Image: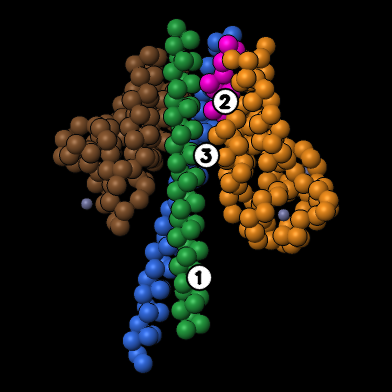
Chain colours: A brown, B orange, C blue, D green
Amino acid sequence: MNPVNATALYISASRLVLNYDPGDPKAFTEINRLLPYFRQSLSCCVCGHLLQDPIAPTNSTCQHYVCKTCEENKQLSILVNCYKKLCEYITQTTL
Amino acid sequence: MNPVNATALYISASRLVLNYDPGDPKAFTEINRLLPYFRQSLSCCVCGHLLQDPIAPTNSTCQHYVCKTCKGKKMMMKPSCSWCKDYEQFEENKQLSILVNCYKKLCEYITQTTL
Amino acid sequence: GASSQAACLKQILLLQLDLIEQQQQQLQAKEKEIEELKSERDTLLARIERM
Amino acid sequence: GASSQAACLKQILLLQLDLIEQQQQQLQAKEKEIEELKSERDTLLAR
Ligand SMILES: [Zn+2]
Ligand SMILES: [Zn+2]
Ligand SMILES: [Zn+2]
Ligand SMILES: [Zn+2]
């Protein structure tokens, strides 16, 4: 079972950062509003922190994901890495 | 029906182009040899041109595509494919359009890294 | 130089994003068709029960 | 400066590439799950 919330939020966030329009005085606050929700979508249901080694149910669409330390889902892993690199690029450039 | 070959080849080509090592005497030839098949997967069967308004068969998974302005015309490969006969069967394919644009931008990058 | 290259990477990146999106929509379609076929299958099973 | 941005964008591009690949393989798996329930449903209709 793939994660819809996570991928959707990654698309929104990446689209927001990479299309940052220098001229829209409202863009930065938008990115700032969307970023914590994207962060929430990839967090561990035990830790609270960002998923270390994601594991997901296959029978439902629970949207509930836990660490291996706490059925491995590759999409969730790639998305965690995506979050990390997007954060890295956000830190590197100024919006 | 989505383009399976086209996405596979896009992944291969993009991975080879993005990990490009000029210190590797083998990488350049690998890219040059994988690359004509990737353009083929996004070529039109009437034109030979890059798929303009991609219309992809839902009829089968033979994966032969034509432009929207190329409906009803004879396909290029002979002997002709048996599955793509029905021209009333294909619909517009969004994934293909995205992949065509991907190819064009990828080439735009390749000409820059070569020169 | 690096401006045209990075500005090229940004565009190919956004395009890749659009692809990921369209694939997600396809996956959702597959999920709905599978679940529909599954409930339909389960109700077609009850046909054996009425012998 | 812009070369750090480029070196980063390359990496995120590769990452998205991996994501696209996984989604492809999953779409294929679900295609198999459909074809199976389709053949199964058909043979059950025949029965
Ligand atoms: Zn945890
Ligand atoms: Zn749950
Ligand atoms: Zn054509
Ligand atoms: Zn054909």
Q: Which residues make up the magenta segment?
A: B14-23
Which residue does the image show at 49% across and 51% down from the upper left?
A: D28
Q: Is residue A33 above or below residue C29?
A: above
Q: In this view, does B53 lie above or below B86?
A: above
Which numbered tag is attached to residue B16? 2
> What is the three-letter code of the residue carrying label 2?
Leu
- What chain letter is assigned to the residue under label 2? B
The quadrant where ligand 3 appears is: top right
Number of callouts: 3
Q: Is residue C5 above or below residue C29?
A: above
Q: How far apart are marks 3 and 1 (CA)?
A: 31 Å
Q: Do labels 3 and 1 share a chain?
A: no
Which residue does the image show at 59% across and 35% down from the upper left?
A: B10
Q: In this view, does B111 lie above or below D26?
A: above
Q: Which residue lies under the disc numbered 1?
A: D39
Which residue occupies the foreground of this view, A69 or A43?
Answer: A69
Q: Residue C43: x, y in percent?
A: 37, 78
Describe residue C37's horizontal placement relative to residue B29 as left or right. left
Which residue does the image show at 62% across and 19% down from the upper left?
A: B26
Farthest residue, direction left = A46
